[PDB]
Image 1 (cartoon, one colour):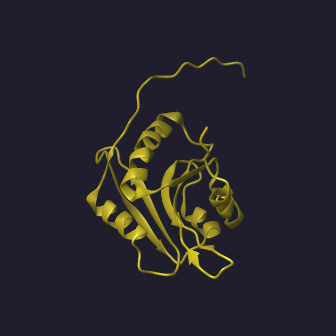
Image 2 (cartoon, rainbow, N blue to C red):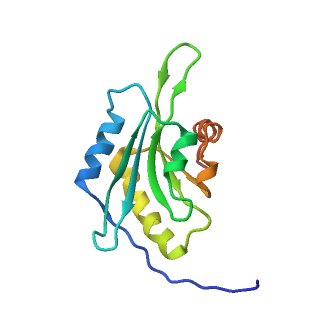
Length: 151
């Protein structure tokens, strides 16, 4: 199909609900050992990012399952990067689950809104997947291994 779409110049940003933020804050300063996953979504009337659900001791391969494969959703997972020496830390990263089968009118909302989130949860690593399926164990260590670069 040879279509030359132009598109509209307008972004839809929102704020993070205190009810959710609180959770994000703890995530980083979590006193647990197992893994975790915090999902977030935006409403049409609430026009504010609220807590969707909280997962515990989950995996990067099973988490994607609890995520939509048609619409973009927010999910904050914390992988476990073990170090040969013996020490192991859980680096908090933001996985922007955006299914290719999603519409642009929505991508703009979650897109502009996402950024803000990365600031609320104080996340340094931010990865995005074109399909919830991609979100897997291997793919996980992949992002932590080779992330963004400056130049």
